[PDB]
Image (cartoon, coloured by chain):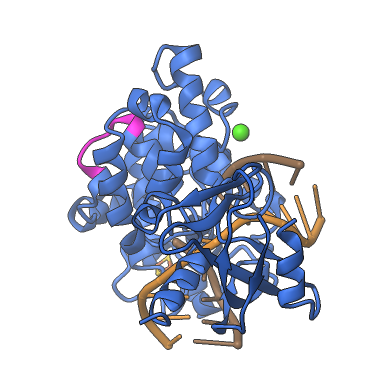
Chain colours: A blue, B orange, C brown
Amino acid sequence: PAREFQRDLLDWFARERRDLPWRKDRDPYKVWVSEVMLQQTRVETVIPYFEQFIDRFPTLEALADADEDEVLKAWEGLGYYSRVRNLHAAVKEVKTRYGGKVPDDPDEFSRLKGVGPYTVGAVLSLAYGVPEPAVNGNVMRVLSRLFLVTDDIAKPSTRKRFEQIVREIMAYENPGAFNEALIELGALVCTPRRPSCLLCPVQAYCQAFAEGVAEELPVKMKVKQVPLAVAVLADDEGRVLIRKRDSTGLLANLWEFPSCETDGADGKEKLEQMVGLQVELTEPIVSFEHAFSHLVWQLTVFPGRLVHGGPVEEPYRLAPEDELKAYAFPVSHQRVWREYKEWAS
DNA sequence: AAGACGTGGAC
DNA sequence: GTCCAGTCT
Ligand code: SF4
Ligand SMILES: [Ca+2]
């Protein structure tokens, strides 16, 4: 019942779509950026980051020419930082290889870093009108209910099935609007919990509603604890010691206060050791937890004084207090410094 | 295939 | 506490 369906949806959308920052226009650059920021992040959280990110990087060219340090800083606190590392690379590519023009061909655009099945569809359909599916979490929840599909949405296979379902019901006339409508619906009406089926504009076509199982869909499956000792080294009144994390793995390329994964009870010994401009640490300042998707950091901050006996090399870099605000730190280490400041005062 | 990969704001 | 809001390997 395509046409019938892809009509009440596009209508509801027309009068119900939220005026979000990235919806001011259909510029591929703006769209691409927002589609990447919204991955595993709520709109409310993203809005401020988007305004800021665009003010700072108005065009793809600006983003491409932008240094990498500045880019991570604009993403500071958003999470899954590899998203911006990939976007920065993909953009640098679009300008050097495609003349600052975003490829409008699924195959071409899909080769860029960070661009997956969903992003290919989202950007190209919303910006260029390419009839490709834009299946994300919200969409799978909506489609699993409309068509009462019980396959584990976690399986790529399931996603593929859903992508097939979209190709057979999308308004090939206006794919872009059709793809957003489906997403808004999942964001505003067909919510994870307590879906507002009574107010939904496509209840007529929903099998899950007819069966009374809407709240049970979609179907999906269901971490490692890690002790971390952190050292805040301060100079004879001034600079503190920090280092740029490895470019691969956890919190890649972000700055942090020197630390070590004790994986046990090493403690101040572990940190005092890693030093090898030596130094010694005092008693802890505070211990707290910080969660990631796949692990939890049980942090322990250790105060300390630095004594210069050599140059600051390797990953390390000496930094004056008033300059820490220039470096991008994970939320975890932003608290390490917060706690530290409310300690010495 | 399924673990890696941040962070926060409803329930 | 729990449940989300995609891509790479
Ligand atoms: S009827 Fe209810 S379950 Fe079906 S799509 Fe609308 S909100 Fe989702
Ligand atoms: Ca791809």
**Does residue A170 show up?**
no
Q: Is residue A125 magenta?
A: no
Q: Quadrant of the C terminus of chain A?
A: bottom left
Q: Position of residue A274 (x, y in %)?
A: 74, 60
Quarter of the picture for ligand 2?
Answer: top right
- Give the quadrant of residue A300: bottom right
Q: Is residue A25 magenta?
A: yes
Residue at (46, 27) in percent of width and height: A91
Outermost front residue: A309
Q: Is residue A171 left or right of residue A292?
A: left
Residue at (48, 55) in percent of width and height: A139
Residue at (29, 55) in percent of width and height: A47
Q: Position of residue A286 (x, y in %)?
A: 55, 84
Name the one closer to the observer, A195 or A251. Answer: A251
Name the one closer to the observer, A307 or A184. Answer: A307
Read off the magenta span: A23-29
Residue at (29, 30) in percent of width and height: A27
Whether residue A293 is situated above or below residue A30 in the rendered picture: below
